[PDB]
Each structure stands twice: as C-alpha cells, then as structure tokens.
Length: 302
Ligand SMILES: N[C@H]1CO[C@H](OP(=O)(O)OP(=O)(O)OC[C@H]2O[C@@H](n3ccc(=O)[nH]c3=O)[C@H](O)[C@@H]2O)[C@H](O)[C@H]1O
Ligand SMILES: Cc1ccc(/N=C/[C@@H]2CNC3=NC(N)=NC(=O)C3N2C=O)cc1
Image (cartoon, rainbow, N blue to C red; front, side, top):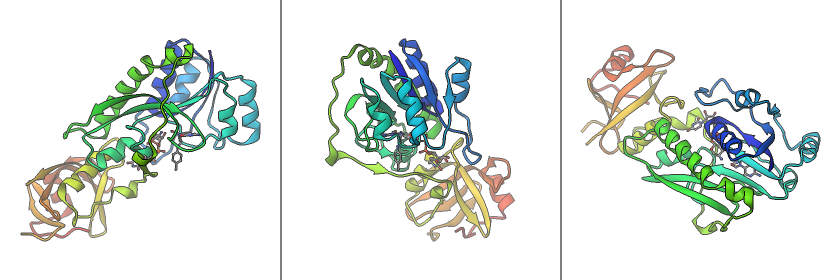
C-alpha cells in the first residue's frame, strides 16, 4: 500500500516508524521547519525521512495548486497525518481512494483542537488518550477508527504525559494499521454534543495570576514544565519562570509567605515554587530563586 504523510514531532516520527513496520510505502512526507521559540527536544521527522530515502518537504502552504498537483501524481492510496500543524484541504484529502487519517492525543471528541497534551494538564484532567480518526475538512472531527485511554497521575507533567501518549500512540498503530491496510475498520461518527475545542497556545498563555486557586496555578506549572516554555510571573519588571511546584494546604494573594520554602499565597491555599529561574538565568531551587529576586517575607508579585 502507498501513502503520502503529513507529520512533525515525536508522534510524527512514531507514526512514520509504524507505517514502515506495518509495510506501507511512504511516497513522500510533508513536515515543518523548527522554530526558535519552541525547544526542539523531540524527534526530527525530516532527519527520519532523509535517513530512509523518503522525499521530504516543509512548504509553508501544502494547499497551493503545484503541491496539490505533485501529491496527486504520487497516487497515494491512503493519507496519514501525525501531529501536522496546518489544515490540508479537501482537494488533497479527496486524492486518496482508501481515505485519510489523523492521530490525535485526546479522548476525541473531548479536547479537539491544538496542544491537547497541554490543555488536559491545565484543566487538571484525571485521564486522556490517543485517537486515530478519518481526516475531513473540519478539524479533529471525523469518525473514530480507534482510541486508547490512559490515566494522568497527579505528579505527571507535560514531558511525562507526552511519553505515555507516544507509548499509547505506537500501540494504537500496532492495533490498527493492518486493519486499515486490509480494508477492515469499524469507524463510528463522533458525538458532536460531547465535543470540546481548545485553541492554539503561546508562551504568554502561561502567565501566573495569584488570585486563582493554587491547584489551578499548579496545573499550569505542570502543563508547560520543561521542555515546554514554563509558567511565569513577575517581580517588578523581572520575569521569572516556575518550573515545578507543590500545593501546600492570612497573606493577600500573590504575596510571598516564606522564602525557604519559597511559598506564595494564592486565592485559595499556597503554591511552593520548588524550582525556577529568573529571566534567562540558570534553573535553581526556590530558596535560591528568592535570594536572586530580592524577595522577602511579604513581597508582592504581579
Ligand atoms: N493534532 C494536534 C495535536 O497536537 C499538536 O500540538 P503541538 O504539537 O504542540 O503543535 P501546536 O499546536 O502547533 O503548538 C505548538 C506551539 O505552541 C507552543 N505551545 C504549546 C503548548 C503550550 O502549552 N504552550 C505553548 O506555548 C509551542 O511552543 C509551539 O510554539 C498539534 O496542535 C496538532 O497536530
Ligand atoms: C485552529 C486549528 C488549526 C488546525 C488544526 N488541526 C490541523 C491538523 C493537521 N492537518 C489537518 N488537516 C485536516 N484536513 N483536518 C485535520 O483535522 C487536521 N489536523 C489534525 O490534527 C486544529 C485547529
């Protein structure tokens, strides 16, 4: 079976890895260029393809006609997206007779959209999953071919959850790809009244507002802990990042209760800044972070 593939990130790499094991011919892979703001810790889909002799591109707009045209000539039987970031129109999606699929890290139709890895940790979800589905004009909405559910633990952060999502993702593809290759899918439409959609995330989305409950602020620390861009606050004009934290069950919110442990009063309870860095400084424990910041007992953040 012949395939053209749209992939990036660790999921991109495992997807391609799974396609090749299961015995497909990946005729070409589309991907993206890396960006300076996003710590690139993950597998490179472009290195993967080169490694295996597959043609690889990263056009900013795959939906431009010339690209539609090169894709149509490759005669993809099936189309696979694994963690690609832009929409692929119905023109490219129609070109595959056996159809097109996407692999997505959520219990669809919950957490459609972007960065569900991170969104579920922000919202303090106790479980999540991986879904493989028909890829249609409308984002993350086509019929579900398979789904594997996995539990989020309280001590989990973005990096630990991501490796569980990838582990789950590879299994899903072992449990799915032969069936797709042979012509044997139970696809079920997604239930629209259950659906949720969460949008694009930026570093600025992890600003810490200390009027919130601590466990809310703690779940933001967890959702973008390193290698994500880190939840942050300010001391004066000084930005500083909270890399890891701990909820500790009469100081007003955003006030430094103690500086060792470095403990900030929130709206409800208190959050311990276990580790953090000031501006572009090195990472340190919280007691040291205070000293560098000039924080004292009773200091006010924004
Ligand atoms: N099917 C979806 C599955 O999740 C992917 O998320 P993504 O890989 O993070 O990619 P993206 O949404 O584009 O977001 C990444 C950008 O967003 C930044 N980001 C991501 C999460 C977050 O919590 N904060 C943040 O700033 C990253 O640093 C980077 O700049 C894709 O959204 C879809 O493929
Ligand atoms: C705002 C936004 C923008 C893009 C997006 N997902 C893009 C990604 C990549 N390309 C896709 N192509 C198609 N035709 N359908 C999909 O569901 C797609 N996606 C599914 O993960 C999700 C939300």
